[PDB]
C-alpha cells in the first residue's frame, strides 16, 4: 500500500507499517529500559518514556509539506489494534535483555499508558481520528496529537489529553503551501483557547524560522497553554534555542519554564493560562 521507494526510507527510519498506519519506538526508549534514562517527554510532562507509543493513522498522507490518493481508511477499532500490536512487537525485542531491563520495566512496557499520534503525515486526515482517541482513552491511555491545523473542523471536536498544532510559519507569505490552507489554520488557532490543553510547537531553521518575535502575534492570538520551540534536525543548537526562547519570553505572555538539551527543545508557559505541564 506504499511505494517501495518510500517504504525503504521508512524502514531505514525504523518505522513499523501496517496499511495506512505506522508506529516507531522513540529512540529514547532503549535508554530508559537499559540506562534508566528519561526523555523530554518525561521531563516536561511526567510521561513514562518506556510506556509511550509513537504512531500515526496516516503514514504518508498530508496536505502541506503527495500525488498518492488517500486510502480506504480502516475503522478506528482496527487502527487501535494495529498500533498496539505493532508496538508490542518492538517491545518483544527486549525479551532478550530481561536480565538487564528487569521484569518490572518490561511488564510496564508491555502495557503502554501514553500514545503520541505525531509520527508522520497528518493525523486529522484519518476520518475516524476522534473515535480512535476516545478508544485510547477508554483503555487507560493519555493522548497527544500533533496537527497542522488545516482541518479546523476535526480539531474542534477531538479531545486529546494534549493537542499540538505545529506552526512553523508566522504569516501568509512565509508559509510550500496554499493560502486557503493558512486561512483554515487561522480559524483553528482562534478556537484553540477553548480546548482543555493546548500547545503550539514550532520547529525553527536558520534564515527560515529564526525571527521568533514574528510569531508573537499568532502565539498571543492562539492563546494556548504551552509553546514548544524545537531545533529542526547548520541546524540550530540548544543555546540558540534557549536564547530564542528568551526573546519570546521577554516579548510575549509565554514564559520559559523548561528545556531538554538531548532533544534541543524549550518549553514556554502561557502566563495567563498557567496549568501544570505535569500530567
Image: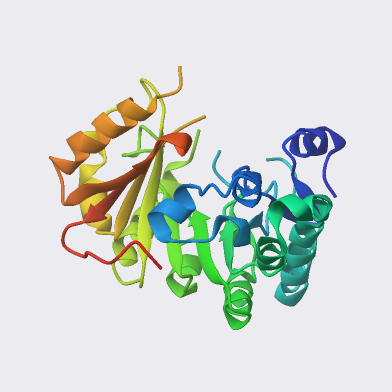
- Looking at the image, residue 11 sits to the left or right of residue 198; the answer is right
Residue 260, horizontal then vertical, whole percent: 40, 41
The C terminus: image quadrant: bottom left
The residue nearer to you, when weighing 77 against 179, is: 77
Q: Can residue 168 be seen in this view?
A: no
Residue 262, horizontal then vertical, whole percent: 47, 36
Q: Quadrant of residue 104?
A: bottom right
> Residue at 68% of width from left, 55% of height from top?
58
**Scheme of image coloration:** rainbow
Residue 270, horizontal then vertical, whole percent: 22, 57
Position of 221 relative to 153 (above/below)? above
Residue 167, horizontal then vertical, whole percent: 39, 45
Q: Which residue reaches farthest left?
A: 250
The residue nearer to you, when weighing 179 against 88, is: 88
> Residue at 21% of width from left, 46% of height from top?
217
> Residue at 79% of width from left, 39% of height from top?
11
Position of 120 relative to 136 (above/below)? above
- Looking at the image, residue 101 sits to the left or right of residue 125; the answer is right
- Looking at the image, residue 209 sits to the left or right of residue 155; the answer is left
The residue nearer to you, when weighing 109 against 141, is: 109
- Looking at the image, residue 225 sits to the left or right of residue 25; the answer is left
> Residue at 59% of width from left, 50% of height from top?
32
The residue nearer to you, when weighing 240 against 261, is: 261
Q: Which residue reaches farthest front?
A: 99
Position of 219 relative to 7 (above/below)? below
How many marks are shown on the rendered structure? 0
Q: Which residue reaches farthest top?
A: 234
Q: Is residue 29 visible?
A: yes
Amino acid at each position: 500500500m506504499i511505494p517501495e521507494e518510500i517504504y525503504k526510507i521508512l524502514r531505514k527510519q525504523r518505522y513499523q507499517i501496517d496499511g495506512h498506519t505506522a508506529v516507531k519506538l522513540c529512540g529514547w526508549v532503549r535508554k530508559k529500559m537499559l540506562e534508566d534514562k528519561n526523555c523530554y517527554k518525561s521531563k516536561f510532562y511526567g510521561i513514562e518514556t518506556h510506556r509511550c507509543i509513537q504512531c500515526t493513522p496516516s503514514v504518508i498522507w498530508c496536505q502541506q509539506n503527495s500525488q498518492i490518493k488517500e486510502p480506504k481508511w480502516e475503522e478506528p477499532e482496527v487502527v487501535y489494534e494495529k498500533i498496539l500490536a505493532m508496538h508490542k512487537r518492538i517491545i518483544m525485542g527486549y525479551a532478550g535483555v530481561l536480565d538487564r531491563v528487569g521484569e518490572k520495566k518490561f511488564k510496564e512496557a508491555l502495557e503502554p499508558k501514553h500514545v503520541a499520534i505525531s509520527l508522520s503525515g497528518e493525523p486529522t486526515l484519518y476520518p475516524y481520528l476522534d473515535e480512535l482517541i476516545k478508544i485510547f482513552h477508554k483503555n487507560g491511555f493519555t493522548t497527544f496529537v500533533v496537527s497542522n491545523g488545516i482541518l479546523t473542523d476535526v480539531i474542534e471536536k477531538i479531545e486529546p489529553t494534549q493537542l499540538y498544532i505545529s506552526l512553523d510559519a508566522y504569516d501568509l507569505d512565509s508559509y510550500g503551501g496554499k493560502k486557503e490552507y493558512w486561512e483554515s489554520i487561522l480559524n483553528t488557532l482562534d478556537i484553540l483557547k477553548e480546548k482543555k490543553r493546548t500547545c503550539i510547537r514550532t520547529t525553527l531553521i536558520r534564515g527560515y524560522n529564526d525571527d521568533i518575535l514574528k510569531f508573537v502575534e499568532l502565539y498571543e492570538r492562539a492563546d494556548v497553554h504551552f509553546i514548544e520551540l524545537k531545533s529542526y534536525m547548520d541546524m540550530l543548537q540548544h543555546d540558540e534555542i534557549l536564547k530564542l526562547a528568551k526573546m519570546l519570553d521577554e516579548n510575549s505572555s509565554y514564559k520559559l519554564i523548561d528545556d531538554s538539551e538531548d532533544s534541543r527543545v524549550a518549553l514556554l508557559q502561557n502566563e495567563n493560562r498557567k496549568i501544570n505541564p505535569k500530567l
